[PDB]
Length: 256
Length: 256
Image 1 (cartoon, rainbow over the protein chains, first blue to last red):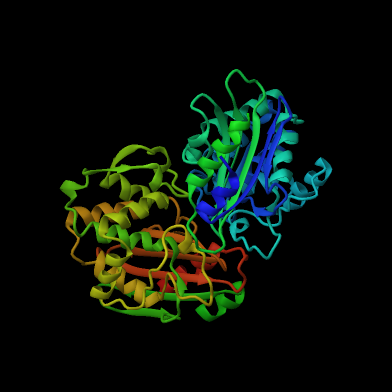
Image 2: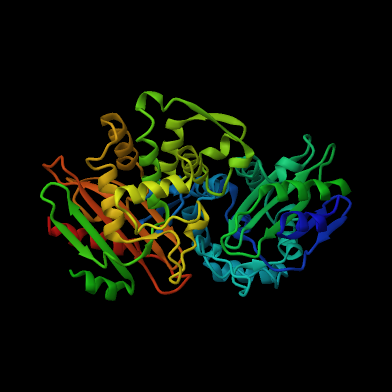
């Protein structure tokens, strides 16, 4: 197969970065191109919070309020003017891409400002968190706001989680969420051999920016394969096509 | 307060149209001004499909395939390759802003084409459906694609649900999906007294386009008040302020 042909075929753009955690083999097509990462950012945001907040403390509470409410928050919507623990807050973010849960998680971290420098400290001078959800989705191929290359964002998912500074309990919490998230069944999950497991977090933005990042797990393999697939179209209101992600997933997984 | 002073207080554009379906009294403000409708239109599409499917046949199933899946489908994301009843579809979209659902419903009608002939048949040549869910969220103060105006949208809801050809069951079914959803809690629901039952549907687009349409029930009245508030800011990335919606619903309501 060929990723290049996939672009002619689908008239989209492909940003790929696969890093085997075992071999250390890196497959990449356009991994140094900037694309809108979209809601996939919530892996980074909640991995960071897990760095500071111990698992024995995820029972803690935060009071959700009116100003904390944003469009598209399936669960947190039922908590307006109420409390909720961090665990439940982080599950909403990952299981449902709840926006109220992500923004609250960001504020607890100290704001976009903090998330940003942590990236820097992590040694990531590419990812550019500038806005909160839902605004981070208004992508413009002219701007850099809320963008990242596949190799940059790809390494960050690695350095934060795989070879992370997280605990073993937090790490396994996150991964469970990402494993049971039914939102990516028509993307990567739909393209990796039946046997492989995927801990994912997808997204979509303007310009038909459909993405999916996941920690894939081959047969008999213990170390996943970090797989960041970022894609996009030439036009603002173009409809994306998950098939392209599913197909890009299998062209690349052939190498692993 | 005054609608002209809240635009100052929040630096936004308020568009209002409240219709007292009993006396016929109207309260307007920038009623002829095009505002993006966003998901408020999910109330139109479901209403339309409920004019051609008697309640006793909402249990008719339709298959959901990978192909049907789109971003933000909290419910329908779990039906990849599963059948689902018409009733379930409506609930999904009406209660969760599920887009895979809103699009299934649009498909069941005969497409935006049918939806469109109907709006013309209702005497609505203002509402401008062009794109689908999600893309219809990408508002452009320049474009007129997927826009309506306070009065046009208000009246269309009136001719459709409020005293329109849906059946008793079908009208209670839809109004219940609107009364019981927890997403307009901070919007119109906030402003009017708890004596006022509120059945609504919200939406949010670019340029902080936070809208909210409802059929508000004054304490001691079975006749509803069609309240249509559409608002927005000048910049593509601004943050919305539901307070603006609440306050507006509070003042506009003083006049009824």
